[PDB]
Image (tube, coloured by chain):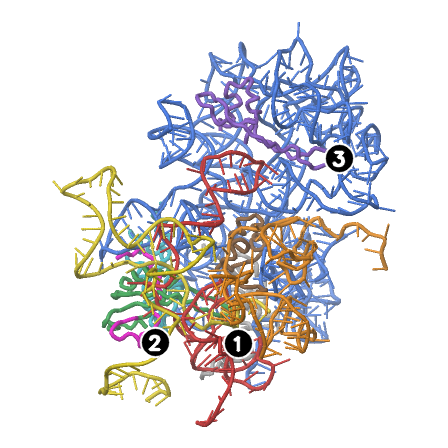
Chain colours: A cyan, B purple, D brown, E green, F blue, G orange, H red, I yellow
RNA sequence: UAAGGUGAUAUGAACCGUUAUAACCGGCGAUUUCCGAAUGGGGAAACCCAGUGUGUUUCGACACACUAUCAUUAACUGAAUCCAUAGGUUAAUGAGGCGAACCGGGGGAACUGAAACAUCUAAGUACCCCGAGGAAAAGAAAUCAACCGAGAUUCCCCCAGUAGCGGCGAGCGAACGGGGAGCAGCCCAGAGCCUGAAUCAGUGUGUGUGUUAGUGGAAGCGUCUGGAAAGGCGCGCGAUACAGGGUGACAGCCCCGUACACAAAAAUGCACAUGCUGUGAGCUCGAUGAGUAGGGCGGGACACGUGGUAUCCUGUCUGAAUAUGGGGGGACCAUCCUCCAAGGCUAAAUACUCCUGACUGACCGAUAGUGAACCAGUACCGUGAGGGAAAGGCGAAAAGAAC
RNA sequence: AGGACCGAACCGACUAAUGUUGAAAAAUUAGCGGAUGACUUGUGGCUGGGGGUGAAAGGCCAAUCAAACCGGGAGAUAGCU
RNA sequence: GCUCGCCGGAAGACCAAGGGUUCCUGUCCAACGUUAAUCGGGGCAGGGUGAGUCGACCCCUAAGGCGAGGCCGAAAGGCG
RNA sequence: UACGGUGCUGAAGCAACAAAUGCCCUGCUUCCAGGAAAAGCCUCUAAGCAUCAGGUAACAUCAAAUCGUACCCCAAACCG
């Protein structure tokens, strides 16, 4: 949920969720698989959050 | 480089044999070595002999050691 | 940003459609403020040889920018600039100089 | 006779050598004029 | 097998090309493409831990495919880079077709 | 604050979210595909491989983490040499890396005004090269005079274009003498008494106030003509608001200004008050680091361009004396005078506007202006080193061929 | 054996002829050698201003350089229509 | 179909000057093939060139780069 | 049959004769202008390990280190 929503969490998505959150780009983002009436381009409009966890990790270890 | 106690010298000037004639006189071209330092050996010690001429009140150091100080 | 706030009712006066009045509007960055769509006889294009071939000639982007009138209600287009005071705690909604807000 | 213009990579180093033109003060000024102060690009860096 | 590695950017989608028809017979010599990160070692480590599926040999391919979109003669090249990967003998598509 | 947005110049189309984190502005952090200036070594600009760890793996591997050259200083260590010392394995900390140019350093011409060209003018300028900061260079005197006196330096008009040097050639071109601007002094070489007392490099806090968002901001209708009446008349009102230019034209009148009232996180200006890590504050008694200076014969810059000769300079070399004076008196020496003992510090006058900022324009309104309106130093030529264009500009809504 | 006598593209430079109003600051056609090396033959890196290698040239060396293709000196000198 | 050409020390071959992706084809006429234009690497819609062995890494060297300490150096710089 | 092609099925299968450009030949000869080092090839030992370690063999395996590989040449996207 966009990243700032779940900041109560003890562990970042790097623990396994990093790949479960990234896999679709090789599994569903080919022709009409992920969708055609109802999805398309995701990873900006909605799905960007995986990248925040990156700079946030370093924030948390650098404190 | 030689007299280095007192630092360096090669000042391009002339000697006017037909008025303002550019013949560069001032370039020195002779070198000497070897004298006894304050400790033990007849060390490498560079001069022309100027450095060692300058020794009539030096006690091996009060000018000698400017290259050796830093 | 305009504190006159996207239900409200405006008119054309600083162009030929002089009096065409309507509400809510359409607001986008450097968008031309159509009042409600003041056009009458201007074509539409055919980028599709399929059945749906856009047959329009009416409403399309009739420009009259920003708003020349502080929201109509009865007569008069001013003072539009007038900032107003505390009503929402993170924004301020306005009407015109004479009548608190809306 | 063999006249003239052609491209190569290994002839560059002593003349058209891009980092050699940063190493000489001769080159350095011209580069900075031609794309740092003067609005522009070079990009032919392969 | 590791999770801290170049994998999550080194791949793209499968390449869907006709050669899946013409050369997959008693083995699954299936096509991919890959980003600017691709040395062979990365794509060798990749497939089985990103798509659940066991493989044998891997090829990397420097493809340099010119494009133009600007009208005026030119556009770009991008990374482009095809690859070939190897779904063994007979597990073919037997649950999904990732086409 | 206030609502929309997805930095665009095909926008199709996904999809954040108009609750008070969607974007976006702002204090301060944070991000690496690899280069990298890049620095283990290599370098043909985008690098191809050393050498040693660490968390941990479906135990293949994995992403990563660092060093160099110097300049100074503690520790360990170390040669032909009992000893000296050079030199290593380190630990510590910074600069080495980068600018059109200012200024400090020196070098830097060629031919050409002189009607002849070896003086010189050319030019201390082309460059190339070394510094290291925002201000400098300097600057606390053998400085200048005539016995009158002045005081770091020199600066401003003079005196004066006077002295005053010459292929007697063309240029260069001084100080005094007067008015002023000025308007203030000391520590080592070191010991006693005294002793966080003066400054300031830091670094936390805080007032007095900045930087900018947030707060704002002026008046009109009726009519004759009428695409826009934003002209004209009416004055039905106005003024320390009548910039320029916007809104399809010409709007005091609708504007966007100007004039005026309030005003933030959280660093941080400057000024001060405090806070704390370090400094030196008050008084005496002491002390004086010469190869430097000479000159006979060199190279020189000074007003004095070759000369009898002028220093304070510079170099082979030789080589004195502590203020019971001589260093020098713009020849040389008197009578006499003034700086001063040859370590080191100083308030003002000056200059670079990197760029962005406020006002002015008998200044450029593309024969052009900072090479520069551009997105032209980009492309039309180039062994190339890179010389750079011909070049303003549809214009309610792109209203851009419905039919 | 021999810088043979006569031999191939790797060599040049004899006078024409369609080379001059160019296919070409250079090359040509039926013709013709030096027959193995006083040959030339090509990736690069030393010769970077008044040049530097000598079959020894006033030819070179960008294609026409007694010094340019430099742009900085400088919109010089200027007895110049 | 049917009758013969040109390159004949082939523009036969794959691949090295980095020029770089503009072949089969699917489609065509300015942004040009000084006739036609159906073809030219024209130029546009797809995609592509699958190297553990090919070769330059290495271990490495005759020419010649850079080089401790240096002998010297005006700042430059040069020879190791 | 997509008019490219693969779908089924399938023969026949010996002796000589003459000649390289090429293979053997870092063979073997013939002449001097006198054809460059490390290394793979193959062994000697210094020290130091030396009831430990080293390498050479049968077999099982693993790693097999960023590239480029498209059109193109005794020669039109080099140059002209």
| Residue C101 seen anywhere in this rendered image of the structure | no
Q: Given contact means CB atoms under 8 Å apart, are the residues at marks 3 and 1 in contact?
A: no
C-alpha gap between disc 3 and disc 2? 94 Å
The structure residue drawn at horizontal position 26% and vertical position 75%, both measured from the top left corner, is E25
Label 2 residue SS: loop
Question: Which label belongs to residue B19?
Answer: 3
Find the magenta span and give its range: E1-29
- Residue B10 lies in the magenta stretch: no
Q: Position of B51 compared to F351: left or right?
A: left
- Check disc 1 and report the residue beneath it: C59
Chain for disc number 1: C
Tell me the quarter of the image containing the N terminus of chain D: bottom right
Residue C3: x %, y % from top left:
51, 60
The structure residue drawn at horizontal position 28% and vertical position 74%, both measured from the top left corner, is E24
Q: Given contact means CB atoms under 8 Å apart, are the residues at marks 1 and 2 in contact?
A: no
Name the residue nearer the viewer: A37 or H63.
H63
Q: Are marks 1 and 2 on the same chain?
A: no
In the image, residue E73 above or below residue F56? below
Q: Are marks 3 and 2 on the same chain?
A: no
Chain for disc number 3: B
Label 3 residue SS: loop
Locate residue F325: give its quadrant: top right
Q: Nearer the viewer, mark 1 or mark 2?
A: 2
- Check disc 2 and report the residue beneath it: E18
Chain for disc number 2: E
C-alpha gap between disc 3 and disc 1? 98 Å
In the image, residue F322 above or below residue E54? above
Residue F226: x %, y % from top left:
69, 76
Residue B38: x %, y % from top left:
47, 20
C-alpha gap between disc 1 and disc 2? 50 Å
């Amino acid at each position: 949920m966009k990243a700032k929503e779940l900041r109560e969490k003890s562990v970042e998505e790097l623990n396994t969720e990093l790949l479960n959150l990234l896999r679709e780009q090789f599994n569903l983002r080919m022709q009409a698989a992920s969708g055609q009436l109802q999805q398309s381009h995701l990873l900006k409009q909605v799905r960007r959050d995986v990248a925040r966890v990156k700079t946030l990790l370093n924030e948390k270890a650098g404190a | 480089m030689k007299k280095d106690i007192h630092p360096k010298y090669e000042e391009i000037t002339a000697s006017c044999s037909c008025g303002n004639v550019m013949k560069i006189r001032s370039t020195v071209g002779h070198d000497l070595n070897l004298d006894v330092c304050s400790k033990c050996h007849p060390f490498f010690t560079g001069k022309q002999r100027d450095v060692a001429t300058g020794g009539r009140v030096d006690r091996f150091n009060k000018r000698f050691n400017i290259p050796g100080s830093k | 940003a305009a504190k006159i706030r996207r239900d409200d009712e405006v008119i054309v006066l600083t162009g030929k459609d002089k009096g065409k009045r309507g509400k809510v509007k359409n607001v986008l960055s450097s968008g031309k403020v159509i009042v409600e769509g003041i056009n009458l006889v201007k074509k539409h294009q055919k980028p599709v040889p399929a059945l749906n071939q856009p047959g329009g000639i009416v409403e399309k982007e009739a420009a009259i920018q920003v708003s020349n009138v502080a929201i109509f209600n009865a007569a008069t287009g001013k003072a539009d600039r007038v900032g107003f005071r505390f009503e929402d705690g993170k924004k301020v909604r306005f009407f015109k100089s004479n009548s608190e807000t809306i | 006779m063999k006249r003239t213009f052609q491209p190569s990579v290994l002839k560059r180093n002593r003349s058209h050598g891009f980092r050699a033109r940063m190493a000489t003060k001769n080159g350095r000024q011209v580069l900075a004029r031609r794309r740092a102060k003067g609005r522009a690009r070079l990009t032919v860096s392969k | 097998m590791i999770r801290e590695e170049r994998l999550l950017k080194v791949l793209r989608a499968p390449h869907v090309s006709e050669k899946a028809s013409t050369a997959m017979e008693k083995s699954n010599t299936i096509v991919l493409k890959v980003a600017k990160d691709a040395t062979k070692a990365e794509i060798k480590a990749a497939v089985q831990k990103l798509f659940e599926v066991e493989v044998e040999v891997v090829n990397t391919l420097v493809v340099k495919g010119k494009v133009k979109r600007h009208g005026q003669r030119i556009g770009r090249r991008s990374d482009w880079k095809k690859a070939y990967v190897t779904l063994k003998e007979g597990q073919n598509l037997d649950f999904v077709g990732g086409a």
